[PDB]
Length: 284
Ligand SMILES: CNC(=O)[C@@H](NC(=O)[C@H](CC(C)C)[C@H](O)C(=O)NO)C(C)(C)C
Ligand SMILES: [Mg+2]
Ligand SMILES: [Mg+2]
Ligand code: NA
Ligand code: NA
Ligand code: NA
Ligand code: NI
Ligand code: NI
Ligand code: NI
Ligand code: NI
Ligand code: NI
Ligand code: NI
Ligand code: NI
Ligand SMILES: [Zn+2]
Image (cartoon, rainbow, N blue to C red; front, side):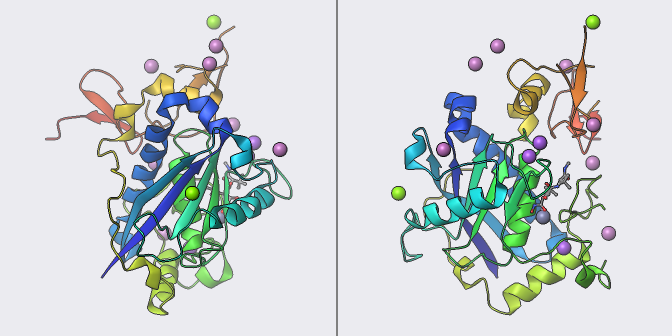
């Protein structure tokens, strides 16, 4: 039995200004990647992330107050989105979850290293099914997937409860090398399973009506190395030096956040990046 996560994607003025006309494709590209992660067999469930609504905030007053404070930005957001949801799931534009993208550097109660935030186990509560995501380039697709984990009640993989069952998975509290063959830990698989078995995802049973089409291409087909560097380091950045770490310009100064090149990214004629390796596009 199939879960469809009817989603609204929302992007603030910083996003509108940075991305201009390409913003909606960018959001859908981010979400296509997350949607793929949620189809991986390791999650032990059938889960379909679909978009039913996008809102861009060209006008700051028509959005929530976005600030550097992650949990307030999230509280501002989760309240504001309520007004934008029809009350029956019968309405084609009714969403089970809302996600805010900002270029604003989000900060926790210690550092601004924070890349996103969500509340835990909220997926079918319209007043709390929310997450906020820092757009630091195409890595935001993983941030999205991670925060939607929490919304599905998965805790961090280093939490006491995950000891029996289990930093190489989606719900690692810090980024490391993701185990591309099994992105979801045994703890994540069990915790989302329990949540749904306990009947907490009843709003995820109904199919989307006229959902917004997700890009079927890999993200590096849309966005070359220079473009990815621009997403992370601003429009004046471009690619420096392959596939494992993207270095970007900033004398020749280059810099990195230690992220991989997006899957699909060209690394020479007839080759492109997959799981941080430059492989042939035609597979033998
Ligand atoms: C390179 N930086 C990181 O890994 C940061 N981690 C995060 O930002 C987490 C999200 C990642 C997508 C794992 C976030 O704190 C979270 O748990 N959201 O629910 C650090 C640990 C430096 C704060
Ligand atoms: Mg509305
Ligand atoms: Mg030089
Ligand atoms: Na941040
Ligand atoms: Na930061
Ligand atoms: Na987990
Ligand atoms: Ni303000
Ligand atoms: Ni493991
Ligand atoms: Ni410009
Ligand atoms: Ni310029
Ligand atoms: Ni290059
Ligand atoms: Ni560094
Ligand atoms: Ni990797
Ligand atoms: Zn987390």
